[PDB]
Length: 69
Length: 20
Length: 49
Ligand SMILES: *[C@@H]1O[C@H](CO)[C@@H](O)[C@H](O)[C@H]1NC(C)=O
Ligand SMILES: *[C@@H]1O[C@H](CO)[C@@H](O)[C@H](O)[C@H]1NC(C)=O
Ligand SMILES: *[C@@H]1O[C@H](CO)[C@@H](O)[C@H](O)[C@H]1NC(C)=O
Ligand SMILES: *[C@@H]1O[C@H](CO)[C@@H](O)[C@H](O)[C@H]1NC(C)=O
Ligand SMILES: *[C@@H]1O[C@H](CO)[C@@H](O)[C@H](O)[C@H]1NC(C)=O
Image (spheres, each protein chain N blue to C red):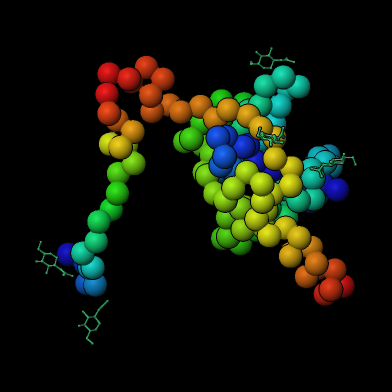
């Protein structure tokens, strides 16, 4: 259902969370097209312990991978 | 241009993160 | 077991919680509205039946 980043539950804006067995991705429902999980394609809401089905996983932050000027 | 404006602050979460 | 994917093509399985989450997303309420209170929704559906 969602990805648990550091204490916060991340749901997908559009698409579903899927995994190849090792890594987790966001993909549109009607066509398999993996995307790295980011704060752009997933919206945070609630807490990590309110929804059943949580899977702990990192959520990439595209705002400052390299932009740490 | 729009009827019914209410003055209020709209936050930018970019700048608290952007310390450097 | 598959929502409406079986009406378009081959039945594609999906957890029923996620199916109802998308069906909530189809009426204008975000997915988390169901997940944060999934038990309440399930109890309401069972009581209605
Ligand atoms: C899953 O995808 C990731 C990223 O492409 C890759 O590094 C990993 O090896 C893949 N694992 C499998 C089981 O294919
Ligand atoms: C899914 O079912 C398995 C076996 O019935 C159970 O161990 C697991 O906790 C369940 N997970 C969820 C998300 O309901
Ligand atoms: C996720 O991490 C928290 C804190 O370490 C832990 O309590 C929880 O059981 C973990 N959940 C999973 C899905 O491993
Ligand atoms: C609503 O009408 C009042 C007068 O009754 C007016 O002062 C106000 O600007 C109006 N607000 C909106 C949202 O149109
Ligand atoms: C908002 O502030 C401007 C001045 O910056 C003022 O002209 C305007 O009337 C104010 N509107 C409201 C809703 O108070």
